[PDB]
Length: 204
Image (tube, rainbow, N blue to C red; front, side, top):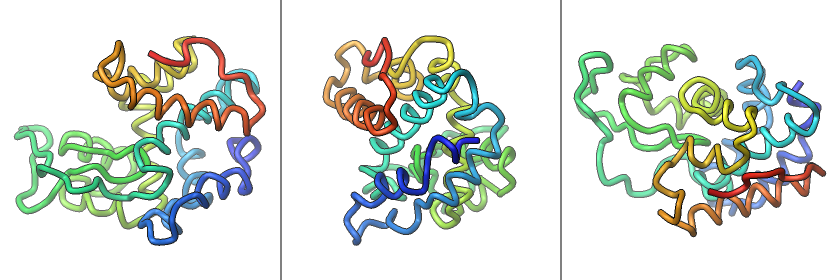
């Protein structure tokens, strides 16, 4: 039912701000988003209309922050391969687990787990997150619903600031006021476009 709250028009509004030279332009598509949203039960379909709108705005505010307004597929100039040696999720030599996709999925352990849920080889083909639009959006919905407290926070009254806490703990309590302001700015803009009150606990 997410397509009922988030129209093609709304999405193109978000996506169309990107410079035409951005890798994300034409990669982040409404079709991929709706496919991803429908694959995870409860995503933007939990609670009253205002609850669903606030979850979706919170999702998109965080996506807009992480991707520079749906501009980037790949993390800019990643400093490392994002390999933590692991017996569960072994790194593949010559592969990089740097941020890819709408919520910048990073690290071998996250790619492995995401791959198992979605249906691709996260350790051996992490580049799929930057090459298939549907897989890319699925990693972000998977992370939101299954690999973080984001969904639980925004559906238990912890508010948008609860989602920031769930994504990047270090930004909160003055850790990085500018990063928080960036996220919060997107959330407020998106709520106003969806005609929903932003609610309580907006920052952190």
